[PDB]
Length: 288
Ligand SMILES: Nc1ncnc2c1ncn2[C@@H]1O[C@H](COP(=O)(O)OP(=O)(O)O)[C@@H](O)[C@H]1O
Ligand SMILES: Nc1ncnc2c1ncn2[C@@H]1O[C@H](COP(=O)(O)OP(=O)(O)O)[C@@H](O)[C@H]1O
Image (cartoon, rainbow, N blue to C red; front, side, top):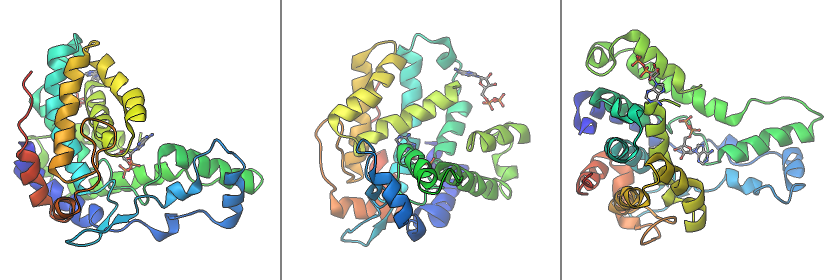
């Protein structure tokens, strides 16, 4: 609903045009030879080829960049926020979440829009830990900037760039004042109701790229705990996330009726934010 607000649509246009519609950065497709050498030594370490994974996806309506962190994902995680909030209020048995007003829900939703824009490849936090440990392992302890810190700083920069010209629109309607805006700009680099809310949106959407075992263990347990041990409420929440994924033609690997990409549908949603919203809106929200 706030995704249809003036602030909402403007943020969407901004993150899409300035970040999400662009290819990943070729300089971050792989490490160099010396870094590669250090990486392979750990047979437990997921392969450096993870740096190049989900680079782009071929689709009837065009080549889709960053298919695992593009506009479909971004809008879905934003979409989920208000529903997650409703479920937390009903089942958590935690007062913090009854402290969750619409405005705080709206801020969380808005901020989710900026949640993946800093990405320059599809590597995980773990891959980045490994890269740095191997840039080290390779060159006698020499430091290099954590790749995820760069992603965070980029996302932060994007956000500051957008809010600078939209303050009269965003304050006081969405952000109460400039210092509240400051806190959220800071939170983008680096445990509150808002954070847990946003983390759970991220968590639920990972069903798109985690297998069932990995998704159910790494992500569903944490949601189940968040909802007062109510497994059933968690499942309904997961069903809606599933349906949003299916509505956008995305792959779903970790929950429900799994599927590969619906290429036709995903190319359409991923290359037109407006089509993506329409499809997401087509899914009935679960009742609490
Ligand atoms: N530790 C992690 N495990 C799994 N997925 C992650 C992890 N960290 C980030 N992600 C994925 O990366 C996305 C955020 O990327 P991030 O590096 O924060 O980009 P940006 O800094 O531009 O927001 C999230 O949507 C999430 O799906
Ligand atoms: N688990 C929680 N649930 C809800 N609110 C929390 C939780 N933990 C801390 N908080 C409070 O929520 C606020 C989050 O920051 P923010 O929304 O920017 O505050 P403000 O709206 O006053 O600027 C913090 O002031 C903190 O006291």
